[PDB]
Amino acid sequence: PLYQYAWLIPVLPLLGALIVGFGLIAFSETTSKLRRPSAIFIMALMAIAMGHSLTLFWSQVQGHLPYTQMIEWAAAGNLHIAMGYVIDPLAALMLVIVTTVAFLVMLYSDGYMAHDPGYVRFFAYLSLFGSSMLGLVVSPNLVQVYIFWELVGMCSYLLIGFWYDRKSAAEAAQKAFVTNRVGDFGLLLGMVGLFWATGTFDFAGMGDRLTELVNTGLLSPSLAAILAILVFLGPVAKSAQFPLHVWLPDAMEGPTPISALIHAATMVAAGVFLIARMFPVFEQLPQVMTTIAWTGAFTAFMGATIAITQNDIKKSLAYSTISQLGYMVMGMGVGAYSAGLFHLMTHAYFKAMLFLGSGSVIHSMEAQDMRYMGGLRKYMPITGATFLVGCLAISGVPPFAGFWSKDEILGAVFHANPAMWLLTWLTAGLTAFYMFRMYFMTFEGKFRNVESPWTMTLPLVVLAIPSTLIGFVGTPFNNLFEVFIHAPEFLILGGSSVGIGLMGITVAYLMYLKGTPSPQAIAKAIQPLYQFSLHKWYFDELYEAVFIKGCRRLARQVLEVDYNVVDGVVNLTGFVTMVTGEGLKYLQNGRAQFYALIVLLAVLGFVIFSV
Amino acid sequence: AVISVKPILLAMTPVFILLCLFFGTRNGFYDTDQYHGNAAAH
Amino acid sequence: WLTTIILFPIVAALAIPFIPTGKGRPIRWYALAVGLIDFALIVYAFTNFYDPGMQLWESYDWIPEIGLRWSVGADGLSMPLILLTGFITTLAILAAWPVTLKPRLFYFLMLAMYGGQIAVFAVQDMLVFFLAWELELIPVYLLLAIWGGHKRQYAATKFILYTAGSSLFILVAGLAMAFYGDTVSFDMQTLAAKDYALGFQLLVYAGFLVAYGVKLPIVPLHTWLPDAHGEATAPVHMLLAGILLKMGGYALIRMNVDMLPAAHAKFAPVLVILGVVNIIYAALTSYAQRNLKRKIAYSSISHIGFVLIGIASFTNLGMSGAVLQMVSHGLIGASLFFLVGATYDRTHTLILEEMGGVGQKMKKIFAMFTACSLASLALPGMSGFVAELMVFIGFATSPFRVIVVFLAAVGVILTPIYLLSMLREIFYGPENKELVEHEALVDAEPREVFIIACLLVPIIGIGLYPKLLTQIYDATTGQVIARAREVL
Amino acid sequence: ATDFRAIMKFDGADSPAMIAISAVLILGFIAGLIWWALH
Ligand SMILES: CCCCCCCCCCCCCCCCCC(=O)OC[C@H](CO[C@@H]1O[C@H](CO)[C@H](O)[C@H](O)[C@H]1O)OC(=O)CCCCCCCCCCCCCCCCC
Ligand SMILES: CC1=C(/C=C/C(C)=C/C=C\C(C)=C\C=C\C=C(C)\C=C\C=C(C)\C=C\C2=C(C)CCCC2(C)C)C(C)(C)CCC1
């Protein structure tokens, strides 16, 4: 049956890429001119994976218990290492999300990539991405949530640096790799600690052993807390949360399909995915849930504040998705396990729609700047309508899914620690503002400066269907999402969000559509907080000043010590045994009488210390 | 269960020897198209 | 078998001086056939290699007047490295096709140091060990001084001087342990089964250390490495960086953990802090260095710290992490320095800021070099990460081991800094102007791609299912560490 | 030295005084740690 060849899911795409990789290295010209059949081959592989995952998801919602099939990977005398797969319902959900988004985006990128070199290497990278993340999801243990959690990082390095002809992509890829290696430093120390203390890594025994040990002594209270925030320092890098957020928007120098996978709930979700599968390390530690929550909250306020003053559409959606990841991490912090993943399962669809629509408009712009693209929708009906739907999703207007997601999380934040409410609330207002000036500046008005495919547009509709219909698996009258995903009246609270969103959309309508206030003179006047938040909260300059200079100076501080204080000391040995020879030969002077001296006077000292 | 390297090696190394002798013939840049040098790095 | 393995390359090398030619072509095929036949002898003598001790040892008697015996012996701890040298020196010869300057001497010295590298592992006599350790000097000296580099004078001279003056206490130490009692042993086993007092255990240990810490360069005992690995062509370098450092590590294991365990237990913290110093030091000195080759040499110096930590641990896992790191770096650095040699051959330049965007026309070396660079750092799916992870786990499982892990994991951040900065400086960006008018090398002739593909298959096969390489020495390392814990 | 002329362009790092008070820190660091390790 199924559940035996579940390991087959990462292998088909990988294999595809592998073959195509051997086709890009050997037989380069053929596979470079063999564009579309390789594409649909990789697509068939991902489609088999998608059908397999869908059948698993159906067999798991219908009813079954999890089926893990592990194997011993690295062995030694007493201890062991396990590396296999488990299929719990959360894994199946994330699996189907990954597969569907990857299939649709692969079809999209069949059209996004015009006559262009690198049409097959792209799909090779993208199938490797599929394998990597699909293998990350199916993971009983934590060591396997580092292997693929870094394979996805290198694949992001590759995809960002697709256009290696350019210079900005190289720096962006280097940055987005190094920041994730900081995250790896964190999670690696956390793993080595959780193995040092407990003696196993399975996400369930790791909690039983921790609560058992803390019931006794042998480590407490901050000796189980230091190696629990290090684990969280991985998601901070991979889910773009504060303070490791600078890598995500600069990764937008890469293509749009890429930026739609690795900014949907496919890669950055991995962070919160980890936080889902580690609550049996965090639930028995209320000293770090608070840290996680306020981290997510400050991230939300950050991404909401920066995106307003931006003018580049893609680089604005970057801070938007940072903010939404912040909402999810907030929900993870204060208790909620089955409400952060609802926003995840909703955010893997409308944000991808927005990125794909951005790719469509920037492709139909012969750039990238909202200020130089005025009223479209005279030629972009489908893209504009679906962008509008995804824009409604990330704000109020309750029939759409993002309200049903950003009501549960807000309710959880209100019942527990309502001080963190009233900041998230205005932040939702800021979402409603920037996402609708992203529309009124872009798809409505007069086309200021100076037309839509088919393959590029079907995915947007196929994702618009979820983004309007996902909200109805929440809805706390017949809630099915919380029962299928479990951890091991309300109008006064909900309608406030819709009212604040109406405030935001109204302030956006009267300000960019016609502009009866002064969008320029509100920032070309006394107010300096347009410069701030357009220099993106100087963190970038801060790191480039204090940190990148630090190692770059310390390297010389060490290397001259190496080339002078270490090397010169031993070369001095050769110098000494050279000058000794140069100065001792003068004993030999070319005089027989000097030998007559130091022959018999050379001895007669040998008699003095003799008798 | 456990997998052993012995038949893997026995199956790979003849292919390695044959492909080594084969790709020894396949060459290029070093012959005439460029590279007046002599493989010394001076 | 081992005697045939060691003597057939050397004996067949003595035929090269009387071997027809018109320009220099039929020498390299002969050398490659010799290397391939000998590798076949390795892997065919590996069929009858069961997997605890010397699974085959063929002793003889040359000089009974001293105690010298031609005691070859394979082992779980020495057979992977024998395979490694038999594979990687063959691929060095399969990389040295364009050698036109004095090819007879090239393919004689290369075959001489092909038996001079299998012998150091397939030897159990402490005098013949010294002989084989020593006979790497003149061949490497000529390999560096004739072809390869402008500073090759200072490099080769410094190499031979340091690897003679620190090939110095190995004999002294073998003697110092040979005549403690009333038996003229000169044999690994018979001399490991002797009770050595602490008063000179930790003196003979330092004698071994001054030797095994210059070839496995530790804190200042490295300054020969940048000069000898910078002024060196690729196929020379593959040997010099993939086998000899492993020779130091192997001999360190077998002479300081089976044979002086009581002093090992007292000095191991030194090796540990030295290893993390090695990592951070080499990584900073690599990110500072700008040329192209010295960078990767310091990267090797960085990667050896995992070996120091894994040997200076005391569990059954750190040792395997060390050996796995060794077999990993032997496969990684070889491809790295091969690609560096190729890139120099196409550009006739090493310096980074003097070239950029070369990956627009020379867009075959860029992929291979990116892959080997990802393999250098502790990337999962490869053997470079399995070693690091096993080192961390095994060490922490055993200097209050929470600070040294924190300092050794800095390499995880600090390796991609200079590697990816090197990639950015070389291959990314817009093509240079006519300042680079060397005609960007016709992207890696299939013959280079085969080299790196056959170096890049075993590494992935290890990184996915590492037991392939660990099935070899689970028994031997188990016995070694059982002994070293039985003392304590 | 004069070879290290790149983005690595810190001026006050090649002088003998700064090299001395850098080697002091590095040697004292390894020495504090070797004393921490033995004891
Ligand atoms: C039986 C077990 C099976 C398991 C095997 C597991 C290993 C899996 C390996 C899968 C490798 C998939 C990647 C394939 C992409 C190759 C792309 C290529 O060769 O481009 C080669 C391209 C060829 O260039 C392409 O084709 C034409 C060539 O003329 C065009 O002109 C353009 O160059 C471009 O279209 O080279 C370049 O021009 C650009 C190079 C860009 C840099 C790519 C380096 C990527 C290397 C990643 C390798 C990671 C593998 C290690 C990680 C292992 C993870 C387990
Ligand atoms: C010989 C030998 C060995 C080996 C063995 C083993 C370990 C094996 C395994 C094997 C296996 C188990 C296999 C696997 C396979 C895989 C593959 C097949 C993949 C990869 C490859 C390829 C595909 C490549 C390609 C490329 C290039 C070349 C460049 C870059 C890009 C790419 C990556 C694409 C050892 C080490 C012991 C030692 C020495 C000798």
Image (cartoon, coloured by chain):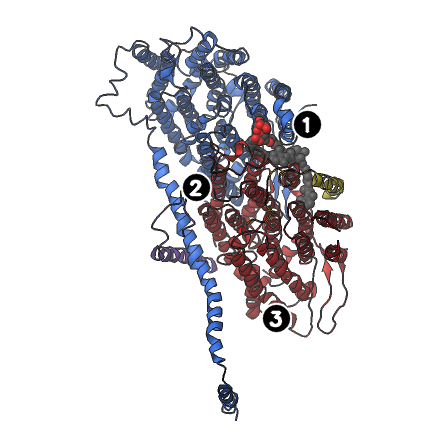
- Which quadrant does the C terminus of chain C fall into? bottom right
Residue C264 can be seen in this image: yes
Image mark 2: chain: A
Do the dots labelled 2 and 3 sit on one chain?
no
Colour blue maps to chain = A
Q: Is residue A124 left or right of residue A492?
A: right
| Residue C102, above or below A109 | below
Q: Residue at x 74, y 72 (%)?
A: C64
Q: Residue at x 47, y 63 (%)?
A: A570
Chain D colour as displayed:
purple
Q: Which residue is mark 3?
A: C176
Mark 2, other Cα within 10 Å: few <14 / some 14–19 / many ≥20: some
Residue C209 can be seen in this image: no
Q: Secondary structure at mark 2?
A: helix
Chain B colour as displayed:
yellow
| Residue A303, above or below B7 | above
Q: Distance between the Cα atoms at labels 1 and 2? A: 38 Å
Image mark 3: chain: C
Q: Which residue is mark 2?
A: A226
Mark closer to the chain start, 1 or 2: 1
Q: Secondary structure at mark 3?
A: helix
Q: How many marks?
A: 3
Residue sticking out furthest to the left: A526
Horizontal and vertical percent position of residue C349: 51, 43
Q: Which residue is mark 1?
A: A4
Disc number for residue A235: none
Specify the amino acid type for callout 2: Ile
